[PDB]
Amino acid sequence: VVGGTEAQRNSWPSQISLQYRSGSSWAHTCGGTLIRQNWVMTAAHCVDRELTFRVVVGEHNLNQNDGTEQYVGVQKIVVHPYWNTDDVAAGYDIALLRLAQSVTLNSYVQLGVLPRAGTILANNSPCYITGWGLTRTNGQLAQTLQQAYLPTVDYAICSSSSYWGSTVKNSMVCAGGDGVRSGCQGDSGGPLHCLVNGQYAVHGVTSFVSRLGCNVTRKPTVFTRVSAYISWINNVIASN
Ligand SMILES: *S(=O)(=O)C(C)(C)C(=O)NCc1cn(Cc2ccc(Br)cc2)nn1
Ligand code: NA
């Protein structure tokens, strides 16, 4: 997250860190959202490489154990069957990870609330991105979870020629693009939390940023639109 601030400890208790084994240790690669005690929602592109993954729930400071974390293996990966790693812009950038055990819920570990199927937010709706992704273009990961206010940019604007044009689809949510605040590498897979009827719900899964930079005017961060996938998510959970 570029242009963010440090989140209060576990104010985003459904945020997870998706990590892969790197030698004798672990490396953060993506965010995700805990949606059942044994299921995480992330981006399909986060699992394009065949690696050993783990999920950390209750995380805040990646470099230090604070007593709130639970670490769990990934037992099954279900990528959307229409995902094409060579065509991010086609969409379908979503995957579900079945965890090797069910995590315990507490003040630090909670299920993320999903929107009702089909929900489209009005332009400029209030949302926050969260993650441990880079804090500047070409920079380094955040040690502690960051948040940034990233209001939505509706499809008509986001898919116009001076923004992302045809690359953005109606199955995506765009947010930000002010040139100061944005998602960045390693926020991918994580949530966009948007306030609806007084409750935050996870409307986006971070999918891509501009190759020109993370915080780039009229290149808002692009998210898979969770509300387009409610039936798919429920079908996967019900059949696994
Ligand atoms: S996201 O918008 O943050 C973005 C820029 C697409 C991103 O940084 N995604 C992170 C990501 C994770 N993976 C899979 C992967 C690739 C290589 C290794 Br060594 C490990 C994991 N690809 N992009
Ligand atoms: Na920690």
Image (cartoon, rainbow, N blue to C red):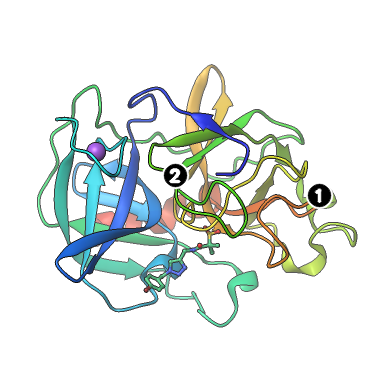
Pick whichever, 171 or 192, lies toward us. Answer: 192
Of tags 2 and 1, the one toward the viewer is: 2
Residue position for label 2: 142
Dot 2, how many residues are within 10 Å of its Cα: few (below 14), some (14-19), or many (20+)? many
Residue 232: quarter of image: bottom left
Ligand 2: give its quadrant.
top left
Residue 176: x and y in percent read 71, 42
Quarter holding the C terminus? bottom left
Q: Residues within 10 Å of mark 1 (few under 14, many from 20)?
A: some
Residue at far left of view:
101
Amino acid bearing label 2: Ala
Residue drawn at x 34%, y 36% is 14
Q: Is residue 209 left or right of residue 109?
A: right
The percent position of residue 221, horizontal first and vertical second, equals 65, 51
The residue nearer to you, when weighing 78 against 146, is 146
Q: Amino acid at mark 1?
A: Thr
Q: Which residue is mark 1?
A: 217
Alpha carbon separation for disc pair 2 and 1:
22 Å
Q: Which mark is residue 175?
A: none
